[PDB]
């Protein structure tokens, strides 16, 4: 494929506008058609539109005409999708893709999550979870990390700066009263948790939150 | 009237083409260029090298990029479109 | 618009089997000039960007292993895997790149069948930080089980509690093909210390008797 | 910046009025002197004084090459004369750098560079993918005026694990 970099996840107030970017690397956008495709939560892929950066000719989907606006800057090798007057139905992941003469989307981007809500940005609360006292051990110890009461997505949860990779199950976030709740489990062997310290690293860039909570017994 | 202004522009260009540029008056040609966003003409395009060689031709970015300028006679004719 | 219909929606095949999924378009995607079918297949792994597998209905994209075969013509197409691996777990879309607008399919979610596994259940009492904050979240992790269909019940002093429970399921694992489930019961400190003996019960297809995990004040 | 040029061209001779300056602002007065090509020679060293305009060399994509050891162009500095050339000594990209270059000399005609023949990586030499197709670049109509009526479209290629996007013009 070819390298494409999209902008960070955006929280937009209902009724405002947002401009998402898609930067190309290693090639010139003048040689490919740039497509934009939205994917709504638990929904299929829906083609928004396409643009030819060589001439600026755009082509949109009948459902996205008037709201979506695709532009392309050749000097910066970038594509831009402008969304005007968003609603709750626009909360989705927007992908930018490249295509040749066949209009087949071969290379994609990481995706930009656009959340349209009125809820305020709330810093998370990171609580460690150690086993209950009196628990019969068996060469398998499970620890937990509860990141409760934050908004909006996303949050990055790692164990020991990401050095603890295997045996980790990070559960997807769930929405309560306009506040997200997430949990993570790490199941190592009962012989290394108290000896070697294990720490839960949580990052919430929307509120510039960086919390490193060390699990402790009892 | 259009051909009259064409001949006038050709004469003013001939004043501009007495040398490589108008000597001590190349800034006048550069003023005309920046006013029309042009650089030379199809008639004397072999002469449209010296303004670029002495940087008299207006360039918004003379560090990089590959292209060509725009004809001044073409811009003059478009001015009467 | 061209209405793409994929069949089936859900699909579960064990490792090494040959799996087939059909895509039917409301209009023939055959161009009589070049005698080529304008259909592409996309693989979207859980939490990833879609990847082009086979464009032009049969032309396999460079880099994709040769175990993916796109067959079919006219209005009916089929994506097949001769030998499915544990890493082929994803959602498969079909998209017509023939006429504007380019419509995607509904999506075939491909599960993987493994040996039926029992959930590893671990209960976690509210952290001291949360106990000093004001709330109290009892967490229950059910790691590495199969199939995904599971039931979770919360019991306080031997009485069922339903309201105030958040649940989160992980997507199927790319290694052991197991599932994980997090259940968080959130209460206030007053009602948390007002009772004793909190139990997390798990009803699964593997065990006719629920797997219970309980903890008391100490 | 990338694949761009400040000033390493010029060095043109007027000679006859054959329209060699046609592509300088080519919005009008563009045309071919006479159309009813031949295979190129090996790639060695270039001569700066006779070459006119930018030399476009073809790897998977078009790329401009500035004079070897680097050149300058700003004004008002004491010195005398410009005479510095560039290098094109290259083998095919999988085992080297690029396929072959193309430029226009001082009188108004085209000179092509190339590599020894042995799908495009195997035996290809110049910008020509096939006899009826060529890689589209901003100065294609200048170096190949007979290909004005060629239709353009976007393709993609591979040259050792790197995807290159191209515009190509073909006869139909
Ligand atoms: C710039 O390009 C033009 C046209 O491509 C060049 O003109 C041509 O130069 C070649 C040099 O090899 C001339 O070939 C010669 O032909 C004579 C007579 O057959 C032969 O005795 C020589 O051994 C040589 O092969 C060719 O005639 C000439 N074309 C003409 C005169 O119409 C030019 O040399 C290039 N370089 C510049 C202008 O610096
Ligand atoms: C590359 O340069 C050398 C001089 O060091 C020269 O002998 C050789 O012929 C050049 N390569 C080609 C393919 O001509
Ligand atoms: C295109 O190919 C046809 C083959 O019949 C030929 O007659 C024609 O001259 C070609 N055109 C160009 C511009 O090469």
Image (cartoon, rainbow, N blue to C red):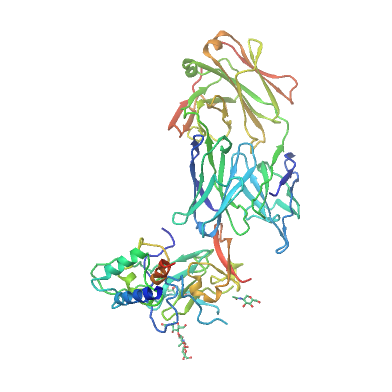
How many marks are shown on the rendered structure? 0
Q: Nearer the viewer, residue B7 or B28?
A: B7
Residue at 47 percent across and 56 percent down: it is A74
Q: Quadrant of ligand 1?
A: bottom left
How far from the left and from the top, in percent, is residue B25? 25, 71
On screen, D150 above or below A83? below
Image x and y of residue C37, in percent: 71, 57
Q: Residue at x 50, y 71 (%)?
A: D140
From the top left corner, tell me how far across and down residue D169 is, in percent.
57, 68
Q: Position of residue A160 (x, y in %)?
A: 48, 32
Q: Of residues A52 and A77, which is closer to you in this image?
A: A52
Relative to A142, residue A4 above or below:
below
Of B81 and C207, the residue lying toward us: B81
On screen, residue C8 above or below A215? below
For this orientation, the residue located farthest to the front is: B1
Residue at figure coordinates x 49%, y 53% from the top left: A72
**Left or right: D33, with C69 as reference point:** left
In terms of image quadrants, where is residue C125?
Answer: top right
Q: Is residue B1 left or right of residue C182?
A: left
């Amino acid at each position: 494929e070819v390298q494409l970099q999209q902008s960070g996840a955006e929280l937009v107030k209902p009724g405002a506008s947002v401009k998402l970017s898609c930067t190309a690397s290693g090639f010139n956008i003048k040689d490919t058609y740039i497509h934009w495709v939205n994917q709504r939560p638990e929904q299929g892929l829906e083609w928004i539109g396409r643009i030819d950066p060589a001439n600026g000719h755009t082509q949109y989907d009948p459902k996205f005409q008037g709201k979506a606006t695709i532009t392309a800057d050749t000097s910066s090798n970038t594509a831009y999708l402008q969304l005007s007057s968003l609603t709750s139905e626009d909360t989705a992941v927007y992908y930018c893709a490249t295509s040749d003469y066949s209009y087949a989307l071969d290379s994609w981007g990481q995706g930009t999550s656009v959340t349209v809500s009125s809820a305020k940005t709330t810093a998370p609360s990171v609580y460690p979870l150690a086993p209950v006292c009196g628990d019969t051990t068996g060469s398998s110890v499970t620890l937990g990390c509860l990141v409760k009461g934050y908004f909006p997505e996303p949050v990055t949860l790692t164990w020991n700066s990401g050095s603890l990779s295997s045996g980790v199950h990070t559960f997807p976030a769930v929405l309560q009263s306009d506040l997200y709740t997430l949990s993570s489990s790490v199941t190592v062997t009962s012989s290394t948790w108290p000896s070697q310290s294990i720490t839960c690293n949580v990052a919430h860039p929307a509120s510039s939150t960086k919390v490193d909570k060390k699990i402790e017994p009892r | 009237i259009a051909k009259d202004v064409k001949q006038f522009y050709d004469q003013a260009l001939q004043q501009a083409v007495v040398d490589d540029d108008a000597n001590n008056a190349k800034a006048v040609v550069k003023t005309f260029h920046e006013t029309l966003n042009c650089c030379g003409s199809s008639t004397l395009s072999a002469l449209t090298t010296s303004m670029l060689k002495n940087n008299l031709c207006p360039s918004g970015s003379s560090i990089i990029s590959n292209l060509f300028k725009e004809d001044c006679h073409q811009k003059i004719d478009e001015l009467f479109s | 618009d061209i209405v793409m219909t994929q069949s089936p929606s859900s699909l579960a095949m064990s490792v090494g089997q040959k799996v087939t999924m059909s895509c039917k378009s409301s209009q023939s995607l055959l161009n009589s000039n070049n005698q080529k079918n304008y259909l592409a297949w996309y693989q979207q792994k859980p939490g990833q960007s879609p990847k082009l597998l086979v464009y032009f209905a049969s032309t396999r994209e460079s880099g994709v292993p040769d175990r993916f075969i796109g067959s079919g013509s006219g209005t009916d197409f089929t994506l097949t895997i001769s030998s499915v691996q544990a890493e082929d777990l994803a959602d498969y879309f079909c998209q017509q790149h023939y006429s504007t607008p380019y419509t995607f399919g509904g999506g075939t979610k491909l599960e993987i069948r493994r040996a039926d596994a029992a959930p590893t259940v671990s209960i976690f009492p509210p952290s001291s930080e949360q106990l000093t904050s004001g709330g109290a979240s009892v967490v229950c992790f059910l790691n590495n089980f199969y199939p995904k269909d599971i039931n979770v019940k919360w019991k306080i002093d031997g009485s069922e509690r339903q309201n105030g429970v958040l649940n989160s399921w992980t997507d199927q694992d790319s290694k052991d093909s197991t599932y994980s489930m997090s259940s968080t019961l959130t209460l206030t400190k007053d009602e948390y210390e007002r009772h004793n003996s909190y139990t997390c019960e798990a009803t699964h297809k593997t065990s006719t008797s629920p797997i219970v995990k309980s903890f008391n004040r100490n | 910046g990338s694949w761009h040029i400040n000033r390493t061209a010029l060095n043109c001779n007027d000679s006859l009025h054959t329209g060699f300056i046609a592509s300088l602002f080519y919005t009008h007065s563009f045309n071919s002197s006479g159309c009813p090509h031949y295979p190129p020679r090996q790639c060695g060293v270039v001569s700066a004084k006779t070459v006119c305009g930018p030399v476009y060399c073809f790897t998977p994509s078009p790329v401009v090459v500035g004079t070897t050891d680097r050149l300058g162009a700003p004004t008002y500095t004491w010195g005398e004369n410009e005479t510095d050339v560039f290098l094109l000594n290259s083998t095919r990209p999988p085992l080297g750098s690029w396929f072959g270059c193309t430029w226009m000399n001082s009188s108004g005609y085209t000179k092509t560079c190339g590599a020894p023949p042995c799908t495009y990586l195997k035996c290809g030499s110049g910008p020509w993918l096939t006899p009826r197709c060529l890689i589209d670049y901003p100065y294609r109509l200048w170096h190949y005026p007979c290909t004005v009526n060629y239709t353009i479209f976007k393709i993609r290629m591979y040259v050792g694990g790197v995807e290159h996007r191209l515009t190509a013009a073909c006869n139909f």
